[PDB]
Length: 106
Image (cartoon, rainbow, N blue to C red; front, top):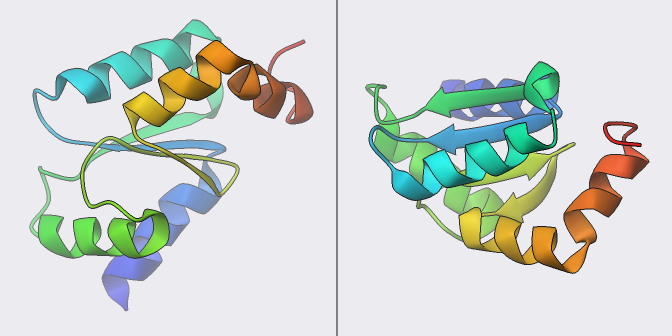
């Protein structure tokens, strides 16, 4: 209960929600790509490794998204997925489209 509620609040309060771990190159890459769209003001990055309930958080992220790995990325509560999913969306125009619909990029 408590873990799910805590994860949900992060995804709800923040248009761009990224779950990450320490020293995680694909986390860093994904976050960098998102900040490249000037999304900082609407991003939250949570380091779930620095948390006593890492496994519970990962299990819930898998229930929500299909994978327990980080990074795990949500945009307005919709699942993007991991960094590779973000790269695909970015390269194919889908990321920009998501962001335009949210008023985050012109």
